Image: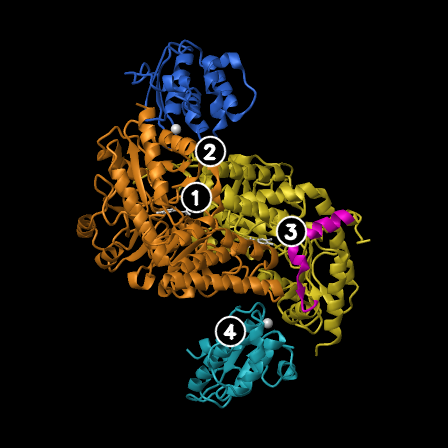
Chain colours: A yellow, B orange, C cyan, D blue
Amino acid sequence: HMRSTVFSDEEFSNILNDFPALKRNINGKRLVYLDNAASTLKCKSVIEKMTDFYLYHYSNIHRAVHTLASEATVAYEQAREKVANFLNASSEEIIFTSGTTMGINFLVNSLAKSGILKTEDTVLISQVEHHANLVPWVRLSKFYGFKVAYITADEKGVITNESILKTKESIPNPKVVSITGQSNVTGQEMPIELIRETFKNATLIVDGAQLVPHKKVDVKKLDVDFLVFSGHKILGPTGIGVLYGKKALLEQLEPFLYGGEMIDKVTFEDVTFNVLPYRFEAGTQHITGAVGLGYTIDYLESIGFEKVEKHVEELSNYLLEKMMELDFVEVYGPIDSSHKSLVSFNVKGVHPHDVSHILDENFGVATRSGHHCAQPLMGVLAKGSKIDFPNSTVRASVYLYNTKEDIDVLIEGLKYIRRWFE
Amino acid sequence: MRSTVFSDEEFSNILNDFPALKRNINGKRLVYLDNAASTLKCKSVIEKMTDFYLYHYSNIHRAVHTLASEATVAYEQAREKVANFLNASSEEIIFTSGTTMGINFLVNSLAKSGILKTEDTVLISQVEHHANLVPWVRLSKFYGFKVAYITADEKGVITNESILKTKESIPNPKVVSITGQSNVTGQEMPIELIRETFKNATLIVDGAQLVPHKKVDVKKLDVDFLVFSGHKILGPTGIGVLYGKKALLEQLEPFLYGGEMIDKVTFEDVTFNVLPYRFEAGTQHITGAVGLGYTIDYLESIGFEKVEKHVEELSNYLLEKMMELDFVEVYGPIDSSHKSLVSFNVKGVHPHDVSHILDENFGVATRSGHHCAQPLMGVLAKGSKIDFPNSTVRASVYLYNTKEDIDVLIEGLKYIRRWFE
Amino acid sequence: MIYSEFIMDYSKLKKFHGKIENAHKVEEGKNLSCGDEVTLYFLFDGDKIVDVKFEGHGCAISQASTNVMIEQIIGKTKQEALEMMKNAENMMLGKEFDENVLGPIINFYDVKNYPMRVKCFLLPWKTLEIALK
Amino acid sequence: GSHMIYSEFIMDYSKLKKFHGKIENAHKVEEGKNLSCGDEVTLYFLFDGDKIVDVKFEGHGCAISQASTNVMIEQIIGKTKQEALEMMKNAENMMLGKEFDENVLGPIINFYDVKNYPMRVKCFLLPWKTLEIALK
Ligand SMILES: *Cc1c(COP(=O)(O)O)cnc(C)c1O
Ligand SMILES: *Cc1c(COP(=O)(O)O)cnc(C)c1O
Ligand SMILES: [Zn+2]
Ligand SMILES: [Zn+2]
């Protein structure tokens, strides 16, 4: 009676109950939160364990023998293990960071400082990359002398199998391949196996920020060399991200940041480094964030991650279908099974800012409006546009606590903006 | 009680804000004296973060919907609170993940911007924490600048004379990066003397230990940069602050690149946002910033001046009682520059054993080891009159601590002297 | 609410769109307001502003504010244009300002109750400011 | 007296001097990493083929790391490198809370309770993890 093939009405109702923000009203209308691709809402039971930790079991970690230091170090190392188990990795391959953005910057610098990414080598990324997986490579190419090349996208922003094989032909042996696991604009889940086997000798990095929150990722079976994501897009706390790297590669890397915890021996003239993974965590980490990320993983697992994945699939399809029925909307991305999570679109005659504004103020609906931290992809979309393209986009994106009813409200709102609003 | 600063009732309300203090270890109340590593958290501040996370949370700056607006306002107001706390302009306050990151930011960006080049010297001190030592030393290999040290004496003290004599050998260091207060010796450093002696250098202060208990006015001190960490001042983990003079910040290459810090991006080129956003790459620790703001409001409502005095009073008491012990070696200045903490060793007992018993049998929490200052340990070694274990125990006080806490420490140490006799 | 008749009218106004070929000053506005684009083109003669044109995609608040800013500065001087922008800025940041200088820039007053639309209003002015060194 | 971790066995072996020193002209010398917060062990071996004749050590340490070291030495004197690296693995196994062989360990079993102190395990293992690296 809530129109899920995945969850029964009771268990679904228990899930929405975990998210107190869903009880906010904006001018009389309940919150319809469709901005999950920027960040997600937080689960009460997960936040309460985080606050329990801060107030009762908190202290700095690793380098003391007292009761609270012991408890916190254990909690923190178990969070590392939960994240490891979540990706099918070993815990010495899991590195906590401040977020996706940091993880990528970590990798450009460290790969260059370690002599893996040498001057004149090529880094291959796609045209649909988020600024986090573009701006570092572009800018630092100028300090370390490597080159940046692009797997091109089509008019709707799609990355086709043919574009990938075509780029193999022009650029057969890129030292590094850095690719999104799923675009935050087009919703396209990238064909990572095809990319891995096509560039079998590249150091392959996957930006998993949109992918990890709703789809099982097994880092061994994908055989990615590096994978990054952010806790805040998977119900988790802010300030916390993850960098998986293969043990054999991580062993070869110059640390990115230096300081306490990550050293072994320090003299005035010399430094040596700690073992993995501590070598890559300089200074006090986001201790409570990592612990919270662990409890967040536990929460999702208590629901069943396969159910979350199927529920988001089912919402994704529905959103796509309803958006496609509208004659006054231009939609971006593939119209196929690779499209998940989010739909970017424009309303004919109306700037995204006004679309998103009116959806919030008049219908309580939350959506992003703008570049979505992908300026260069905006120019690719502009060339395929059949309207007066504003160099930006509206974006609605779904997650666990959303419903088909959420999406129908989006639809009502957009028809209202179309009809009125000269 | 036994405070010249807080009445019995006022102090008692303060202690009850920290639930951690209600915990017991083998029958004894927690005596938390490891504040120099991190501090316990206040219930009111955490309840406010909970509310934020659960009812006002979204990502910031780039959306027009209700929650994005509340969260963006909250975040920028937190920046303003940190600015007012340091007497800086809000555009001069960058949020980071910690002191450590802030220092790495500076080394990398000062080198990438051409300010810290092959033929240039960074002057730091022998008492520096690994976070203000290891980046300079390691990155010297990659960028070719020199590293020089202001020297400490047998007890770890940086004297005025040492500072002036270094000025004779090292007349024009391009960068000076010094701690505002040592996390091992407790020495509050003469920042004003440092600033005037090296008037032409770019001056960085590692304020991680100083800012939590002494008001810092960055305009009056005239530092070029200051860093500190929220978790040392009752705040959330994963959040720090870098302050920089506006005119210097404008000239710096960003350290980290990504969303938010850009202005224009094409496939081939990139331009940068304005201050401070230019130095905040990607989604920051939003909730951390907001909680650091609520932390500062909490401290200001107690009166930061009272915090500073209460810490002074406890330190003087700690120092007095530890100096009366015939079986202990104390490091650091043992004068009016000595604040917050005492490093020491028990004659013939290794620091791990001292801290273990203190914890297990007295509920007293302390650190034991190098305290993230390994090279300082060799300096203290040369001045040791005992058999020096290349480590020390460290006891450190803060707001929610009392003289009775220090007394339990003293008792513990007497028990420990007998145990290994 | 935020979308008054005055604002919608000025968003639609077509009188100032364009390039000025061989303009005295071309100032591209910065991405400080997502994909609101304003590139201002100026003609001068000393301190007077004879003409001003602008190009770019933008939301109704941004387009209106640009067209209104342009109306109120055409034939007016560089020096007074900068105090007019300080007052337009002060109006939004909840400060003292007074109406006198702004005239009908006052109709954008309610925009301040929408903290995320403030950027949309300010973009043109912030770009006028950089353009007038 | 009454105690918690500092058992009568641990206190006795912490005070042992028998193995304190270096060997002049040594067939092996391995310095321990500082993964134990300023406990130090440097091990000096004499071998005589594939067996182990004499061991000695220096370093400032902990009651627990010192005791662990003394007992480690006393049980690998007169044993093969593999008749020692397997104690090591059991020693480690005990400490990390995994199954292990009681008889291989002999009186090392007296360190069992130390498994209950997450932050003192490093102190126990230091000499063992150093002996591991010293023999590969
Ligand atoms: C949101 C996002 C990022 C940035 O993550 P931060 O937490 O902001 O560092 C990077 N890549 C993709 C694909 C994203 O969707
Ligand atoms: C704690 C501390 C640091 C490092 O703080 P993190 O939060 O671990 O980055 C640096 N310097 C001093 C003096 C400190 O006390
Ligand atoms: Zn706008
Ligand atoms: Zn030890």
Main SS category, magenta section: helix
Q: Amino acid at mark 4?
A: Glu
Instruction: Provide the chain ID for the residue under circle 2.
Output: B
Mark 4 or 3, closer to the camera? 3
* Residue at numbered disc 2: B27
Q: Is residue A252 above or below residue B201?
A: above
Q: Amino acid at mark 2?
A: Gly
The answer for how far apart the CA atoms under marks 2 and 3 are is 54 Å
Q: Is residue B314 left or right of residue A261?
A: left
* Residue at numbered disc 4: C28
Q: Is residue A155 above or below residue B97?
A: below
The answer to whether the residues at label 4 and label 3 have Cβ atoms under 8 Å apart is no
* Residue at numbered disc 3: A182
Residue labelled 1 has its Cβ within 8 Å of some atom of ligand 2: yes
Q: Are marks 4 and 3 on the same chain?
A: no
Indicate which disc residue A282 carries.
1
Mark 4 or 1, closer to the camera? 1
Q: Is residue A20 magenta?
A: yes
